[PDB]
Length: 284
Ligand SMILES: NC(=O)c1ccc(-c2ncc(-c3ccc(Cl)cc3)o2)cc1
Image (cartoon, rainbow, N blue to C red):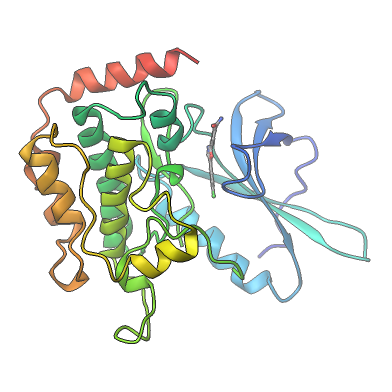
């Protein structure tokens, strides 16, 4: 029932595009009556697209209520004249402290402390576990899709169409080749992506960042599992990276297994890390 969706006129205001265009037509929005912020995903909707759109709303209503997923608020339809085309606004939680990509880029030497990596990675894994239990694959885990609220809460965004995006966080099994002709996403594909995101937090960029995207896409299923460049890291972090980045997804551990891994499981400085992150956020 899309006919019941209200016009957003004096309920939500569009401020500006959020980020720069990583998310596309996603806006910084304001609740008119309170001044509260929201992230507004905007899309042109045709008569045939109506059925596919209904399933998106339902997914957000059921799965976004976990603390490691940005909350869904509601939907609006800005009806255009009979000469088409209507706009659909999906209003979600605004994560003011921005992405994990921004967090590494704003940090001296473009590297995060190991205890920060463990905390963020665990929160990613906790969000993935909620999705996987409900038979949902995120399909796009990367630093830009992991956001921080003003209270250092870690939240996942943009889970699941004519364009292929960035290849750098893609698991080998999602890239079709002669051996793997029918490339398909598995729940374990999100675990590889989590591992690449952990390397991104550690080095400021994913593994084949210096390659043309088409060359990286060719190299991912052919190259051995990527490794951390520095030897400074603990034996537990190298082990976590090794766990995430098992080449063949069939021997790759589950989200439940990775949540029990010593690097994720053993976090005594958890309380201090949350304060440390909150302090970095306070410095706008
Ligand atoms: N200023 C910033 O860097 C910044 C960047 C991003 C955000 C943000 N909050 C929620 C979302 C979101 C993104 C994609 C989707 Cl699909 C849904 C929600 O993005 C806030 C601030």
